[PDB]
Image (cartoon, coloured by chain):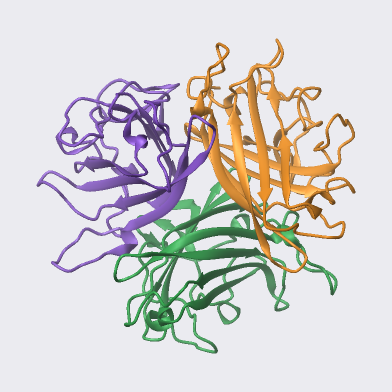
Chain colours: A purple, B green, C orange
Amino acid sequence: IENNTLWTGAKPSANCVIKEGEDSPDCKLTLVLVKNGGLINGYITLMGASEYTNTLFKNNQVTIDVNLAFDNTGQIITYLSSLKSNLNFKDNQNMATGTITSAKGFMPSTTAYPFITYATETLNEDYIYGECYYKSTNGTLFPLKVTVTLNRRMLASGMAYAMNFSWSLNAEEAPETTEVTLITSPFFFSYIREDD
Amino acid sequence: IENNTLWTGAKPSANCVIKEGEDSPDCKLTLVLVKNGGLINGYITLMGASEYTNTLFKNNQVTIDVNLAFDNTGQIITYLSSLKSNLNFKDNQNMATGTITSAKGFMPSTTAYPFITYATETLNEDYIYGECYYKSTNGTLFPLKVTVTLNRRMLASGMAYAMNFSWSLNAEEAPETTEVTLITSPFFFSYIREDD
Amino acid sequence: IENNTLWTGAKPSANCVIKEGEDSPDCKLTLVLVKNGGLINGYITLMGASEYTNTLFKNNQVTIDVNLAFDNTGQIITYLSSLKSNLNFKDNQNMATGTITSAKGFMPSTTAYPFITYATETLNEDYIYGECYYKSTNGTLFPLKVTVTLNRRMLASGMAYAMNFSWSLNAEEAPETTEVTLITSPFFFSYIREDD
């Protein structure tokens, strides 16, 4: 058990909900958070697991969202998050088993990335922009604009941290025509971490 | 305290100077350097804190430079740098208090990234090119080409290492029309580190 | 000596072959792999060391390939790879001396990035896409599309892992006219790692 890593395990089963209103997993979310000094080194990827997700790319303009809300101990609050199974430590290629006593040290810092406090506050320092890709059936690479939001809005009283990801597909013509497994290539990023 | 992290602290006060021939801080520079094996994982963000900086983006072609000069012990030499206060180790969300006995290990390898020795010498292995973004008032994302110069040019007799950053804006038209806090989205990078 | 880092050493001597069917190192390959929790933080750069490699960019369309095959203990399989000299632990700015008794812990996870089990199998999760740059003589920058293939294709019985890199240039017109040193700017990446 390596406690310097908070993740979904390598190659996880459907554990994430991307469809609006849905409650049951419709895709596989791979997320790796690693404590690296004052930073967290992150790794994230999405793999479709339903006709809905695997059809999304028959359109030329799509936006996928995965929202993550954590309590005061860095535990995922499922009813508020797209991810339906809590993260855990590294135990080889899987998620360690048992209760985690605080993963606070893995959360985005509230000093560096604050929560909105007043009506018109923009807080643009709470955003990370980047890019990853989708490889279509014929082999073409479609660029996906990625936006990461750290602690900008709280959604309920027991919520202490937030981490949102969104992938944006805005191309000339749809990538696919058939139902093809939705795969976002590895997105890398880092952020100032909260103290333990 | 965590000595594998050399940083400006999370959310620092104005501490950097971007305007020509100035002495007083006109912007907030966040720089995190973490020791990770033979590498340094870096994070850097800029937040303007003056009328001159928060107005730079009323133009479409802007280049911002933040130059860092260090002594033989990896300490900042303020009169040679844009950053006007030495970096220090991590102590929760702050810069540690106390004297630093060498931070040489956080510096750019001179073996990998050499200093210029002759006149027409280019040493292109000293550059790291990447990209980050500025989000305007109306929500549009402007790309900023980031250049990182490792060592290469030496300025004074006491200077042992250098690290220069430059954000380059080259848009169709001016992102802004008003004075808006300049904000560069997190840029990530890595480099071969100097031995301890 | 630091065994949490596996590399070619900083600024190494010609150690890589980019030419078809060749066996004599015609370029310098800088590759650093650091164990960072469940991930491996990577850094990679190339430098021409022959007329062949330093002439390539006299064309507008070029693709450089660096293939890496490893055995069940993370050791390079030279007859199968482009890197003709094994990697080793960190010893200051050099490769440690001696025999690495297993570098499996630095290998691409077979669970996260599986090998093909049949004919028409795609395994698109085995790719990482990104970008680095080339600074020409006139100072202009040319974007190079980078593609990393993790495992996926097995080539011989003694193979257990793969890590191929490919730089792709596709610009209006050739970056050069003269034989100039080939230098790709640092490409950063992470991947889920194989258990020790």
List the single residue furthest toward the left: A157
| Residue A122 falls in image quadrant | bottom left
The picture places residue A156, in percent across and down from the top left corner, at 11, 46
Left or right: residue B173 versus residue A140 is left
Residue at point 53%, 20% (across, down): C110
Specify whether residue A193 is in view. no
Q: Is residue C92 above or below residue B126?
A: above
Quadrant of the frame with the C terminus of chain A: top left
| Residue C33 falls in image quadrant | top right
Left or right: residue A157 versus residue B33 is left
The picture places residue A151, in percent across and down from the top left corner, at 25, 52
Quadrant of the frame with the N terminus of chain A: top left
Specify whether residue B72 is in view. yes
Q: Nearer the viewer, residue A32 or C141?
A: C141
Question: How many numbered markers are drawn?
Answer: 0
The picture places residue A141, in percent across and down from the top left corner, at 51, 40
Residue at point 77%, 32% (across, down): C82
Q: Nearer the viewer, residue C64 or A104?
A: C64
Residue at point 56%, 22% (across, down): C196
Q: Nearer the viewer, residue C123 or C91?
A: C123
List the single residue furthest toward the bottom: B21
Q: Is residue C168 above or below residue B75?
A: above
